[PDB]
Amino acid sequence: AQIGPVTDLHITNANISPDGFSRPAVLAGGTFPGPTIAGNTGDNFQITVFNDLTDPSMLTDTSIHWHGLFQKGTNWADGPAFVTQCPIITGQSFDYNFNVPGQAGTFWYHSHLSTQYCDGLRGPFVVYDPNDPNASLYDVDDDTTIITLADWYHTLAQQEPIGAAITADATLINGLGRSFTNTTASPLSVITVQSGKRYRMRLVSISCDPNYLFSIDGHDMTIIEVDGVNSQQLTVDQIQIFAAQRYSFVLNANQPVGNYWIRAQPNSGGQGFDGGINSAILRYEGATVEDPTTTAPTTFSNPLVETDLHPLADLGVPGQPFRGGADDPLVLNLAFANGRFSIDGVSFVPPTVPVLLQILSGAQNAQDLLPAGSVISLPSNSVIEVALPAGAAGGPHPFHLHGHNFAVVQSANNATPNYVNPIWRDTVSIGGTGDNVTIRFTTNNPGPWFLHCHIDWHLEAGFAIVFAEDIPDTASANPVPQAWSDLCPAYDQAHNIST
Ligand SMILES: *[C@@H]1O[C@H](CO)[C@@H](O[C@@H]2O[C@H](CO)[C@@H](O)[C@H](O)[C@H]2NC(C)=O)[C@H](O)[C@H]1NC(C)=O
Ligand SMILES: *[C@@H]1O[C@H](CO)[C@@H](O[C@@H]2O[C@H](CO)[C@@H](O)[C@H](O)[C@H]2NC(C)=O)[C@H](O)[C@H]1NC(C)=O
Ligand SMILES: [Cu+2]
Ligand SMILES: [Cu+2]
Ligand SMILES: [Cu+2]
Ligand SMILES: [Cu+2]
Ligand code: NA
Image (cartoon, rainbow, N blue to C red; front, side):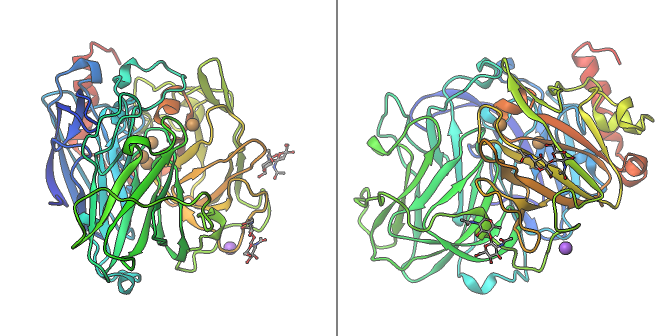
């Protein structure tokens, strides 16, 4: 069952064996992935998070981010540790109480402390639309049509060297899959469909690192949503999905009753499908209970290309139709050396006092804010352009902005910008050497918003900056509850930190 919009959520340690290998984990709701949190557009969510963690090897503190929800007026509930809150300590709880006006689509939630989400704290978050403009395109849309793609590691995250090329041991589809080495025939996930029906498949990357080449043998996929943003219908036979992205696609159950492989090939780790790695099963009602015998093509003739996507609504692009045609045009210098990433010459290391608390305490320009050189102020009610030229090692890097979605004016692997009708989204691959992926948005949401690569190992190695949007209005826009004001004193006391 789905939970929410008002619910408790307990965070616990437990052993799990999703690929046949047992290891301890950090779990929401006792499962991997965690339960789906759901509601309708405009609802009040009150997710009271109970930190019941006791195993220090995966950190006993926690903090949860609601990925892609704008948090307008509730910046304190966004979740990134040391940006909008101090962590919740073990044996305590915290009510994330926020609203979702003007958003409907497919989201997710995850730990936003260190690399803790890799250790298991990740799950879907769906905001349904009772008047969805795409409703007539399918018959079924429920918890059974969510498809999660996850990387899974046998080594615990706090034992992964910082700045290393860290590689997974299994791909998990809906929580199950097989290990790349020492492969055992452990159970595969089954997605069941009825011949003739149409399904809104909500494809969610909960990855800590790899991108996946996702396809379904014999089937094609009609994209209708991108990171929460309704799209024009785009039919493809493969989707390359980067960490933290989401798509909804219509699956027409229009092939002969039978079993079909669902494939998710990561860019690192095990290549191919030997032994049923990187796989799940699409089963039609009435089919024999047996593995598929289907083949992938050698090449995919209609892969997703990001410039083919266009919004369903007339969203346009803010600003003027040329590079630098914005009120505040930025170009970030994104670099890697010696195990650490940097943005504009500064490697991110979380501050002792959360950025939001520094601003509420009176620090009111970005040079007064810590970490020094890691906070850029943005002016209010202004068009912002951010160019993100690629080349730093470890690519392709999926950059994500909190508090906002954005127009993708220039996409990976294509030098031509689009100032007319590009897709809007919240996490974007910045591509390869020589690319100049560029995003635009308008500043109508005061608060400190993290900008970072969503490969969690890269964030941990410093690939982040904070946009302090409309510092002067942050305090009046974001009144804080007493329980939020209590977090930093409790955390600092528990960890013997002075501030
Ligand atoms: C990516 O595009 C940005 C503009 O959005 C380019 O920025 C210009 O860079 C040159 C130096 O390289 C400066 O003289 C300009 O002031 C910048 N802003 C402009 C022209 O509007 C950036 O060079 C591009 N990067 C790549 C790798 O193509
Ligand atoms: C490279 O990106 C550009 C810009 O998004 C794409 O150009 C558009 O192509 C569409 C589809 O044919 C035309 O309707 C638009 O007028 C083009 N816009 C511009 C500004 O040129 C282009 O198709 C992409 N290249 C590839 C190979 O997909
Ligand atoms: Cu996220
Ligand atoms: Cu986010
Ligand atoms: Cu990265
Ligand atoms: Cu983040
Ligand atoms: Na415009």
